[PDB]
Image: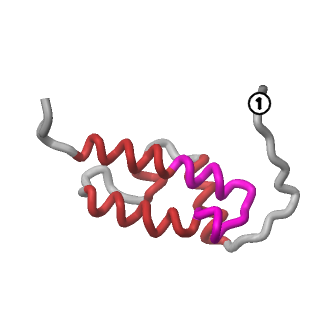
């Protein structure tokens, strides 16, 4: 089947909304996290952290805050993998 949830109620700040709006309308991970394509693991994580807290399901009860948080992960986690310049293992 398919999962579905109703979020009739929506209470949050501009910052949050703006986040979920950008993520859902992001063309890449850099845009989501809000960093440059030439940043380091420390950077990507920094942006992912600050954001995560904002999109966190414990801070943002928004109906989209959930989806947003999910995107971030796929973004950061992915980017990081690329961050690696040389193949450590193999």
Q: Is residue 82 left or right of residue 18?
A: left
User: Is-magenta flag for residue 67?
Assistant: yes
| Image-quadrant location for residue 41 | bottom left
Q: Position of residue 19 (x, y in %)?
A: 58, 61
| Image-quadrant location for residue 35 | bottom left
Q: Is residue 86 left or right of residue 66?
A: left
| Image-quadrant location for residue 21 | bottom right
Q: Is residue 4 above or below residue 39?
A: above
The residue depicted at 31 percent of the width and 50 percent of the height is 37
The residue depicted at 40 percent of the width and 50 percent of the height is 76
Q: How many marks on residues?
A: 1
Q: Is residue 61 above or below residue 84?
A: below
The residue depicted at 43 percent of the width and 65 percent of the height is 49
Q: Nearer the viewer, residue 51 or 5?
A: 5
Q: Is residue 79 above or below residue 1?
A: below
Q: Nearer the viewer, residue 18 or 6?
A: 6
* Kind of element beneath mark 1: loop
The residue depicted at 14 percent of the width and 35 percent of the height is 89
* Quadrant (top left, top right, bottom left, bottom right) of the N terminus: top right
Q: Residue furthest bottom?
A: 13
Q: Residue furthest top?
A: 1
Q: Is residue 70 left or right of residue 45?
A: right
The residue identified by callout 1 is: 2
Q: Is residue 48 left or right of residue 14?
A: left
Q: Position of residue 36 (x, y in %)?
A: 32, 56
Q: In the image, which residues are magenta?
A: 55-71
Q: Position of residue 12 (x, y in %)?
A: 72, 71
């Amino acid at each position: 089947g398919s999962s579905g949830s109703s979020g009739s109620s929506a209470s949050f700040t501009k910052e949050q909304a703006d986040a979920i709006r950008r993520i859902r309308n992001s063309k890449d991970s850099w845009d989501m996290l809000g960093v440059k394509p030439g940043a380091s693991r420390d950077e990507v994580n920094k942006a992912y952290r600050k954001l995560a807290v904002l999109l966190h399901p414990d801070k943002c009860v928004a109906p989209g805050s959930e989806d947003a948080f999910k995107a971030v992960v796929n973004a950061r986690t992915a980017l990081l993998k690329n961050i690696k310049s040389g193949p450590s293992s193999g």
